[PDB]
Amino acid sequence: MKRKVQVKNITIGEGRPKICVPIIGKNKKDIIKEAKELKDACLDIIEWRVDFFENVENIKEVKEVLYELRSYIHDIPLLFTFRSVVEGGEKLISRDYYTTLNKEISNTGLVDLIDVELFMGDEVIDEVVNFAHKKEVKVIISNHDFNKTPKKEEIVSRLCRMQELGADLPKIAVMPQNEKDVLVLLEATNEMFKIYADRPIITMSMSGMGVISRLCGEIFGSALTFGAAKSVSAPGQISFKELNSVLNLLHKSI
Amino acid sequence: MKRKVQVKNITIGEGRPKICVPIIGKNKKDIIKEAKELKDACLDIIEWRVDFFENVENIKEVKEVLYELRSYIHDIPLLFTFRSVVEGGEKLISRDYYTTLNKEISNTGLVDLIDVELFMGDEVIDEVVNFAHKKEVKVIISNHDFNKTPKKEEIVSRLCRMQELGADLPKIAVMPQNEKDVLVLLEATNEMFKIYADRPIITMSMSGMGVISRLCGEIFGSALTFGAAKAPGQISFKELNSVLNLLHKSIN
Ligand SMILES: *Cc1oc(C(=O)O)cc(=O)c1O
Ligand SMILES: *Cc1oc(C(=O)O)cc(=O)c1O
């Protein structure tokens, strides 16, 4: 069977996919303003994309925001994510600081999950994952491809590697070059879900063409889907309110 | 550059998929009541599933419903469909009457489209298609598999055959036995759409597992999607419409 991943009072891997919405504010004021817009909406998890925070290199200022943020969102599960430049992020930092940041923040007891990138390598991952687990923090190990959709077996191989590395929630995001690529991502998702996964997984096909992948998790297997805070697309994004409506519509269809 | 299909003021094959809702009333009063709920609603096309009509074997009573129905939906495109028993319908009728019914209703000038089944055979199809076209009525040629999802290539072969038989709108509905079957239906749809189609097509994967196929037609290539008026595997048409516009705006 499979393990479920409990964060706060939310059970990832059970029922309807959970909706996660990111906070991308550049400063403390904007982050809190974003948080207040999300604290009482129908969403499941809030992600703090800390790589947008201008003072991310100062651990003390990062902690200060985290304290305040925690106080406003109460018991909503919080995912901490520093997305590196190579995988779409906003700020260059060292490998050593990436490790320190994630460890120090996991140590606060204020974050429920952290996102660590597969591409950082086994040394970094082993250190950050083991420490997060010591602090009862759940781990998403993520990988992105912004130019293509790897073959089904490649996608499955990466998700399996993420399980082997101790990810509580393997995550993969790929870019379709055509409509068939969106279907490959969905095919890989379900094969993993059905045959290889012993825990919940997170997958998406990016761009406008890949949006179906954000809607059909309950059927194909993605356990978490990401909505945008605002009601304006990138495009390829869906505002979280509208995403909630679609997920409920599909949950009730069966 | 690909042909669109124009019915009244609705352009099928352009922009978001068009929403079609069936009326399944067993009698005239019930059919009218249903039409009254759909007339000022957010949908594009109304389908009359005439096989549910108890007096379907009386062409004069079928026409009577049609004249009354048109006083309520004068400008909404109307699709006329007698779904046969072999393809999930309610009423057994002869092959001759199936042909007669579709011809006399096409001749009234009061329906914008009719739906005839591919597996009725070329003789029946050729006669009905030819006559419908002389009256400027659009024809959906449909095919259903309630037990399984044929292989991608067989789905494409059927959609191609429908085009060869003069369908204005090829239509296929298949039943998934697993999640991959839903992807097979979507893959066949886009393959047909991009490589072999010279007109709009309509496709769907049935049941709760295939519901996603009713929502993503703009990306994959289905030009019409069917909502329910009031059942697992069906989506109320009211919701269907917000979703389609939401997805139309999210395109690159
Ligand atoms: C988590 C996650 O989500 C998206 C998205 O577009 O919603 C993209 C992405 O790269 C990522 O890591
Ligand atoms: C047109 C059409 O729609 C459905 C549906 O489930 O909406 C099924 C079906 O057999 C058909 O012909």
Image (cartoon, coloured by chain):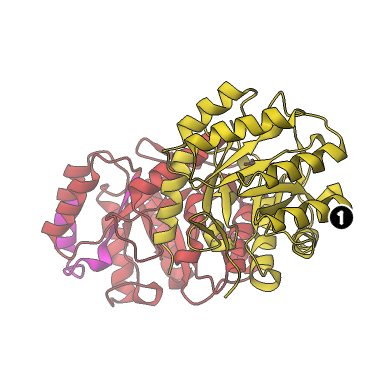
Chain colours: A red, B yellow
Q: Please report the bounds of the magenta region as a residue range.
A: A45-67
Residue drawn 69% across and 66% down?
B192
How many numbered circles does the render carry? 1
Residue, x 42% and y 58% (percent of image)?
Answer: A129
- Residue at (66%, 35%) from the top-left corner? B49
Q: Is residue B93 above or below residue B119?
A: above
Q: In this view, does A107 lie to the left or right of A194?
A: left
Q: Does the magenta stretch include residue B153?
A: no
Q: Which residue is labeled 1 in the image? A: B122
Q: Which chain carries label 1?
A: B
Quadrant occupied by the C terminus of chain B:
bottom left
Nearest the eye: A150 or B164: B164
**For mark 1, does the 10 Å Cα neighbourhood hold few (<14), some (14 to 19), or many (20 or more) residues?**
few
**Regarding mark 1 in the picture, which secondary structure is present there?**
helix
Q: In which quarter of the image is the N terminus of chain B?
A: bottom right
Quarter assignment of residue A155: bottom right
